[PDB]
Image (tube, helix red, strand yellow):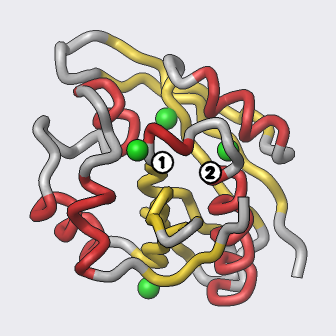
Amino acid sequence: MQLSHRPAETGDLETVAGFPQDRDELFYCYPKAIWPFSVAQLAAAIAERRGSTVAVHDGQVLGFANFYQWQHGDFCALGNMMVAPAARGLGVARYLIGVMENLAREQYKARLMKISCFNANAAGLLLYTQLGYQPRAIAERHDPDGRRVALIQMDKPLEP
Ligand SMILES: [Cl-]
Ligand SMILES: [Cl-]
Ligand SMILES: [Cl-]
Ligand SMILES: [Cl-]
């Protein structure tokens, strides 16, 4: 997995917007989105966020991430994290988290990275644990069917 990264570009939107495969995945990816996902919804998210980045392998955009919160000298929080179905389990999310941690450190002088993960996302919970994130709190959210879900709020220190 040769991976590279760069800021997201308008030409990447269609591909990235195709990453969520069903309403639940979209909810995890982007809770305020409405199924079906679209390039316009993705572009609106990008405009409201910071650090929108794609991961590329063999000429293909395989992952997307950004920050939904950023506080200089303090912390950043992972926003959207989306990975192409064919590329899941291959280190794309791991790679992107590392890139976002560096950008938190460098651009925002962050001491902490926050990651929230919905309870159904076992693969996320397990990966973030492997990367040294620790659970701090559990919040209640509601899914698109109005069912109660648990949001596991995790964090990790970042040094200078
Ligand atoms: Cl930015
Ligand atoms: Cl795919
Ligand atoms: Cl991964
Ligand atoms: Cl999640």
Write the residue at 25% across / 54% down: 17
In the figure, residue 40 lies in which quadrant? bottom left
Residue type, mark 2 in image: Ala
The residue sitting at 71% across, 76% down in the picture is: 110
- Residue 101, image x and y in percent? 71, 68
Name the residue at 66% across, 76% down.
104
Residue at the outermost bottom position: 107
7 with respect to 36 (left or right): right
Identify the residue at the far top of this view: 147
Vertical side of 134 occupied by 106: above or below: below
Name the residue beneath numbered marker 1: 83
Find out whether the residues at labels 2 and 1 contact each other: C-beta distance under 8 Å. yes
Please name the amino acid that badge 1 sits on: Val
Q: Observer-nearest residue: 96 or 27?
A: 96
Q: Does label 1 point to a residue whose CB lies under 8 Å from ligand 3?
A: yes
Mark 2 residue's CB less than 8 Å from ligand 3: yes
Image spot of residue 89 (x, y percent) = 65, 36
Kind of element beneath mark 2: helix
Q: Residues within 10 Å of mark 1 (few under 14, many from 20)?
A: many
Q: Residues within 10 Å of mark 2 (few under 14, many from 20)?
A: many
Q: Residue furthest front?
A: 58
* Quarter containing the N terminus: bottom right
Q: Position of residue 123 (x, y in %)?
A: 63, 27
Q: Which residue is mark 2?
A: 93
Residue lying at 73% horizontally and 36% vertically, measured from the top left: 127
| Ligand 3 shown in quarter | top right
Front-most of 144 and 73? 144
